[PDB]
Image (spheres, rainbow, N blue to C red):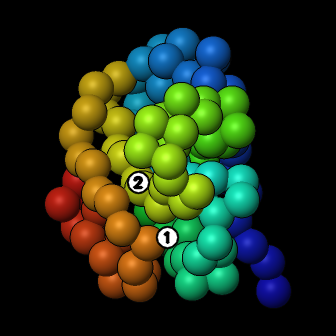
Amino acid sequence: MSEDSATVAVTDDSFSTDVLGSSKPVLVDFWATWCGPCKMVAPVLEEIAAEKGDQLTVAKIDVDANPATARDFQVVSIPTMILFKDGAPVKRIVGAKGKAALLRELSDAL
C-alpha cells in the first residue's frame, strides 16, 4: 500500500512565479483555512489530486494570506478550484460538491 506524492502547496507571493514560471500544466484550488465543509470535500481533493496528479500538479491556496478575497463578500468558506495551463487560465469551477464535479476538470482539461 502506498500513496502519491505529486501535491505541493505554493505561496501567494510566489504563485505566479511558480505557476506561470512552470510551462507544464498546474492546478490550484482556493479554500479557507477555517472552511466549514472540510469533510464533504476532504477525500475529494485527495482522490482528485492523485487522479490527475501524474498529468499535472495539484496545489491549494491559503485564504489566510489573501483575506481580501473572502472578506470582499464576507465569505468564510471559498471552496473553488481553478486550472492553469501554460501559465494561463484554462478552467475555473466553484462549488464544494462531490468528486464527480471536480472530476470534470480533468475530463475537460484533458
Q: Residue at x 26, y 33 (%)?
A: 89
Question: Horizontal placement of 17 versus 36: left or right?
Answer: left
Question: Horizontal placement of 67 versus 99: left or right?
Answer: right
What amino acid type is highlighted by mark number 1?
Ile
Q: Residue furthest left?
A: 108
| The C terminus - image quarter | bottom left
* Residue 58 percent location from the top left of the image: 54, 50
Q: Nearer the viewer, residue 14 or 70?
A: 70
SS category of the residue bearing label 2: strand
Query: To which quarter of the image does residue 27 belong?
Result: top left
* Residue 15 percent location from the top left of the image: 56, 23
What amino acid type is highlighted by mark number 2?
Met
* Residue 11 percent location from the top left of the image: 68, 27
In this rendering, the answer to whether 58 lies above or below 2 is above
- Label 1 or label 2, whichever comes before in sequence order: 1
Q: Which residue is mark 2?
A: 81
Query: To which quarter of the image does residue 4 belong?
Result: bottom right
Q: Which residue is mark 1?
A: 48
SS category of the residue bearing label 1: helix
Question: Horizontal placement of 90 versus 55: left or right?
Answer: left
Can you tell which of label 1 and label 2 is closer to the viewer? 2
In this rendering, the answer to whether 62 lies above or below 88 is below
Q: CA distance from mark 1 to mark 2?
A: 11 Å
Q: Nearer the viewer, residue 15 or 18?
A: 15
| The N terminus - image quarter | bottom right
